[PDB]
Each structure stands twice: as C-alpha cells, then as structure tokens.
Length: 183
Ligand code: HEM
Ligand code: NA
Ligand SMILES: [Xe]
Image (cartoon, rainbow, N blue to C red):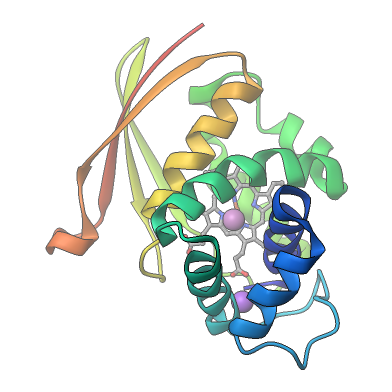
C-alpha cells in the first residue's frame, strides 16, 4: 500500500502508546531496516500486514480491534495531512459521502498512479438506512471499513449503527454491511 497508509499507522501507535512502543512493534514486524515511510511511494502489502500482526502481539489486542481503531483514525488523519479539501468535496452527509467514495478514490488515483482502491456500492433501503457492498483485492480489511463508517459518523455529527451481514471469510462473494443512520 502507499506509504501514507503506513505513516498513519505509525502516527496512531506513537501518539496513543509512545515512541518506545512504536519502535518495538517496527522491530517485531521485521522492519528495523526502514528509517521512515515515504508517503507517496508504493510498498509491499506485506509491510502493512506485518505491522498489524506485530501491533497485535505487542499491544495484546486482536488484529481486528486495531483495524477498527485505525479506520476511525484514517478519517481524521487524511483531513489533516493534505486531503481535507478532497474530503469536503465528497459531501456533507454520510450517504452522499458513500455514493462518492469510488469517485473520491479515482481523484486520489490521479496523484497515486499505482493505487488499488476498494470498490463500494450503495443500495438505499430508506432515508435512514442502506446496504453497503464492499469489494477488494485484499483480505481481511472488512473490520477497517467498520471503523471508517464510524469516523464518517463522528465527521457528519450522525449516529451510525453498522452490522456486517455477509463475510468474504465465510465463503460469500463479498462483504456486505447493513447501515442505520440518523442526525
Ligand atoms: C482523502 C481521503 C482518502 C485518501 C487520500 C485515501 C487514499 C487511500 C490509499 C492511498 C489507500 C491505499 C491503497 C493502495 O496503496 O493501493 C486506500 C485504501 C483504502 N481506503 Fe481510501 N483514502 C481516503 C479516504 C477513504 C475513506 C473516507 C474511506 C471510508 C470507507 C476509505 C476506504 C478505504 C479502504 C477500505 C481501503 C483498503 C484497501 C482495500 O480495501 O483494498 N478511504 N485509500
Ligand atoms: Na504496505
Ligand atoms: Xe485506509
């Protein structure tokens, strides 16, 4: 994934647990050979998977719980590290935001030529609910989508309730989430 993602992980861990913990996790992840992540440079997806697993071991939290926290953090992080206007342009409510997500990644994709973004599709079931279809080239990030939806929730001052109804992990085609929302 692009370094921006790994910088964000480093930043979340450092701010919440301190630099000493961040150095232990980096060492454990097998990355001592990397002084710093380059935001606009492509890295092997392995770098990120090794960091999550090393953080899970060192911090004693399941990888899935860290991915939910990272998903909320990403909403705030991008807005403060050069992408606030891009975010604002994708809208001012949770559902309109999700409709634009493919289009937001296409814009991100101008500047990150080698991006493999997720694909998201909405089916609106009412003015207060939707089904969200998530398809990805990667495994295991559905829990990250749960935290991102909560970050967008805090962003738009909107109560959100998210329940996953289908799992790529239990053989289903792709992950589907059921979302209820409300001002
Ligand atoms: C301006 C804001 C954002 C920027 C600059 C950005 C950029 C990125 C980048 C660089 C990646 C890594 C992909 C790669 O290296 O191939 C990524 C992945 C991802 N992004 Fe976005 N992103 C933004 C906002 C969001 C938001 C708000 C969501 C909320 C759903 C989201 C959903 C995801 C997911 C689930 C992935 C995991 C990759 C996958 O599933 O295959 N992004 N994004
Ligand atoms: Na990576
Ligand atoms: Xe992300």
